[PDB]
Amino acid sequence: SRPQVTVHSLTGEATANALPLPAVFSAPIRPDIVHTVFTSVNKNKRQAYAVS
Amino acid sequence: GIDHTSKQHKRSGHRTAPKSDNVYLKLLVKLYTFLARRTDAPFNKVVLKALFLSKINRPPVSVSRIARALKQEGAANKTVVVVGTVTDDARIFEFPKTTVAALRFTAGARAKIVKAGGECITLDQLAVRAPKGQNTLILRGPRNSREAVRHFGMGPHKGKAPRILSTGRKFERARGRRRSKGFKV
Amino acid sequence: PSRFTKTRKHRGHVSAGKGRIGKHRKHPGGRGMAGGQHHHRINMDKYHPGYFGKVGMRYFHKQQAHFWKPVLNLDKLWTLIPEDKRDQYLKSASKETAPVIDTLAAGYGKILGKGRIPNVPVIVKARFVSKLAEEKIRAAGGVVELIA
Amino acid sequence: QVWGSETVASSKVGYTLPSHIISTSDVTRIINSSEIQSAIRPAGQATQKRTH
Amino acid sequence: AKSKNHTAHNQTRKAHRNGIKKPKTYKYPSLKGVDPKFRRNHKHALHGTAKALAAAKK
RNA sequence: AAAUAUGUAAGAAGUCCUUGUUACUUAAUUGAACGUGGACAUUUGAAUGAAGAGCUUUUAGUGGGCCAUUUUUGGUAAGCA
RNA sequence: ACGGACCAAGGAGUCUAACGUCUAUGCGAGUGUUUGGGUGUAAAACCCAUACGCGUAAUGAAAGUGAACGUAGGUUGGGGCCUCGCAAGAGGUGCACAAUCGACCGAUCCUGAUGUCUUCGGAUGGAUUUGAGUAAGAGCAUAGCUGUUGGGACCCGAAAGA
RNA sequence: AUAUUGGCGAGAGACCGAUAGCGAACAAGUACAGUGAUGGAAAGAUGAAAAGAACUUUGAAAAGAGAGUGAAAAAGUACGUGAAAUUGUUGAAAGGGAAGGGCAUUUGAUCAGACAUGGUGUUUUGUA
Ligand SMILES: [Mg+2]
Ligand SMILES: [Mg+2]
Ligand SMILES: [Mg+2]
Ligand SMILES: [Mg+2]
Ligand SMILES: [Mg+2]
Ligand SMILES: [Mg+2]
Ligand SMILES: [Mg+2]
Ligand SMILES: [Mg+2]
Ligand SMILES: [Mg+2]
Ligand SMILES: [Mg+2]
Ligand SMILES: [Mg+2]
Ligand SMILES: [Mg+2]
Ligand SMILES: [Mg+2]
Ligand SMILES: [Mg+2]
Ligand SMILES: [Mg+2]
Ligand SMILES: [Mg+2]
Ligand SMILES: [Mg+2]
Ligand SMILES: [Mg+2]
Ligand SMILES: [Mg+2]
Ligand SMILES: [Mg+2]
Ligand SMILES: [Mg+2]
Ligand SMILES: [Mg+2]
Ligand SMILES: [Mg+2]
Ligand SMILES: [Mg+2]
Ligand SMILES: [Mg+2]
Ligand SMILES: [Mg+2]
Ligand SMILES: [Mg+2]
């Protein structure tokens, strides 16, 4: 039973509707795995450099 | 001076505080290091060490292996402890209604256990159930079945899988392997 | 990465880990596979017995397509039935409804009898089957239909 | 739909949300579960007295 | 240029540095090398007694 | 025919008792080997010390040596070999 | 014995293809999206089908053959668990692992059943022989140190050859 | 559908930053060497703006001393910042065929902190 999530309006006041957690927020949080994945994926947008 | 009998400042050589930085795993180590300190049950000390082991030292344990252990006399209702991962086995067709505790359950293995009426349990839930390992059973996967162990200790008259990239005819099946060509091994 | 390399730890030490006497020359023993029947004989025989010489018969223009013959053991061959119908067929173990398993479609050429299939009669089609493999199949009440 | 849950598919072929290796992240609460308290032995004083 | 031919200096030091280990004898030593006529009998004798114990303890 | 060096042993994987196996062996329930079951426990089999014991993988450097007492070879001898 | 009159700046184990051991991670009898396609805030990120690569079967030069007699065996030693006992201890179960004897598959040498296009088929049962095998799978991918090879290959160095 | 260190036109980089990066960020394939084929550099930065020092004085002159511009001439066309080797002046110290160094101390020079604390308390002012 995901507890609830309050929904806000563009005017800043909470609306009547409330939604459950999408059950992905309960996934394990692994700082180590994210750190390794981030290190590799951040290298994907790179341009080659070389001396003549 | 001191006529030293043995090497000084020598490490114990046994891994403690496993070098993996899995924060959840460290919590499990944090839990059991408290148990083994203040429970005096030999089960806790065994499990604590088993958490430190490396990947090769934590071979997968098949569900078929679980079935064999439960078939032992007077072990049907015991709780199975697997410090590692549990892999599904399609070679088996009957599974009992046991409960098992393991670090990881593969999707196939977890489905098989649940479909058999049992439940998959994490190590912490075991601790609250059996703080001193009441009625438990620890299983270990095979270590020598690794491919790398085949080449270990290669030498004359040993037959220990010489390291090779490509296998087949004319790849190390000549002089030195048969008496028609020089000698045999 | 470089910053973890022992080279960074070898800065300031004159030999860079290569020692004083032996040093690190260009190619002290030779290049590549030199010395198999020579100064490197000891390693080659101890660790690679059977390297030198020819043993078999030559095959000209070998096409690795005639020899395509994947093997299947009897502990498998129930995975080839989808999980949805696997429970149905196992409990409804009877003839005149035996599931048809086309091992060729799965991409297997020969059936090998590793052992211990259940007592459910099944119909499996394969290009080849070993003796004991089929004896286990029809002992359960099944039969094999040879296909090509 | 994007990540799935215990009741819906994940919309990515053969994907399932990862599972936790530990039921909860609060070890102190478990240690105070009292199933363990009964099993546990009495404690010292956290600072061994300097003897001799 | 002449050079030292052979010597045994420092050898005992080297051997005793890791110690001279006993061969670590085992129970049930290997039957490799004993007379084969005894083996072919010994195989059937152990087969026979295995059946006898299995039936008696059954 | 020494001295110094050197192999082996000082138990539980032991001792004793009874009978099961075998195509081996015997003139033969005769033997052999492996066993079933039964009995003998810390003075369990000399001294001392054990700092933990056992085991695996991988790899660096090294592969020019020299000196001293004692034994000793060539040489007259050598800071000689 | 060699180099060093002095000072500033530059200056020497890197990168790659293929790999070995070990470690971490993900998945797990499977594993690998990024050849390519769709999509995009556009060399990023996200999604995707078929094959293919390695693994799940090995052994023979090859034709070929192909892994359960049995609780997937017996025996010995085993952490741990269970029972009794205050404990000491006694008994049971004993994964991984270690030793040993067996069992199954392939090769070699034998034995040669039922039969027959009468020369084909090889049943059955053995053998101080042999395999980089089976015996309720562990592998695939990524990354990291170290080590190897081919590369200018730690940096500078020929007399020569075309 | 494929190739393209050339040519033309564009967009970018966990690239280099004037001993680097093309040999060439500059009148660089230039100056220069060789009969010749060929070989081949060094060299970027005042200041916002020259406002680049009118004028006086000493000197033959270059320049110096003043004056002045400038936020700054400790930015003056030898010009941003201006290190080291090496040198001059000033100041201190020691020195009988080296100097330099290690331990401890004398002597000289030079240098930081601790010295309100809370508090008895109002012998008190700006009365708290
Ligand atoms: Mg000391
Ligand atoms: Mg050193
Ligand atoms: Mg080194
Ligand atoms: Mg050197
Ligand atoms: Mg060397
Ligand atoms: Mg030598
Ligand atoms: Mg000689
Ligand atoms: Mg003796
Ligand atoms: Mg070496
Ligand atoms: Mg060496
Ligand atoms: Mg040398
Ligand atoms: Mg000289
Ligand atoms: Mg020299
Ligand atoms: Mg000189
Ligand atoms: Mg420098
Ligand atoms: Mg695949
Ligand atoms: Mg495909
Ligand atoms: Mg391949
Ligand atoms: Mg066995
Ligand atoms: Mg390399
Ligand atoms: Mg050269
Ligand atoms: Mg001239
Ligand atoms: Mg200034
Ligand atoms: Mg300036
Ligand atoms: Mg300046
Ligand atoms: Mg200076
Ligand atoms: Mg003088």
Image (tube, coloured by chain):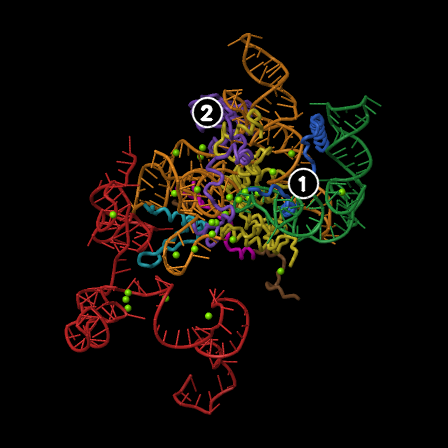
Chain colours: A cyan, B yellow, C purple, D brown, E blue, F green, G orange, H red
- Left or right: C66 in relation to D39: left
Asked whether residue E33 is drawn in magenta, I would say no
Measure how far apart labels 2 and 1 are at the Cα level.
Answer: 50 Å
What is the x, y in percent for residue H65?
A: 23, 76
Chain ID of residue with mark 2: C
The amino acid type, in three-letter code, at marker 2 is Phe
In this orientation, does residue A23 appear?
no
Q: Nearer the viewer, residue C122 or G124?
A: G124
Q: The C terminus of chain B is located in which quarter?
A: top right
**Secondary structure that dominates the magenta span:** loop
Q: Is residue F53 above or below residue C77?
A: below
Q: Find disc 1 in the rendering and name its residue.
A: E23
What is the x, y in percent for residue C2?
A: 43, 50
Q: Nearer the viewer, residue H79 or B157?
A: H79
Q: Which residues are magenta?
A: D6-31
Q: Nearer the viewer, mark 2 or mark 1?
A: 1
Q: Find disc 2 in the rendering and name its residue.
A: C67
User: Picture quarter containing residue G59?
Assistant: top right
The amino acid type, in three-letter code, at marker 1 is Pro
Q: Nearer the viewer, residue H44 or H97?
A: H97
